[PDB]
Length: 53
Length: 53
Image (cartoon, rainbow over all chains, first blue to last red; front, side, top):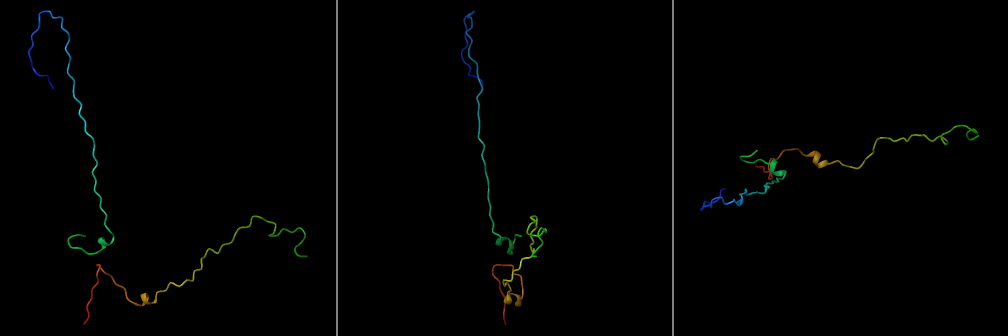
């Protein structure tokens, strides 16, 4: 970003004293793991069902 | 008598191979008379139903 404006008046030939600069800001985020698990018994797959094979 | 004095016999040789029948004899009973006598069929559900008249 940029700094805020302000008053800027200087004396003639001030032998400038060197003002400090500006630096960037570092941001970071962490990773995340999502999962889903399922278990079905063998009997539930052999019997006849309506709407599913 | 009783094998010549210096004859080479099976007593002295050392490289004799073993003899295995290569067949396993199992006579334990495993017959199922009632299961063999009755008929076979297929069921498609946990509960099996039929009718009489």
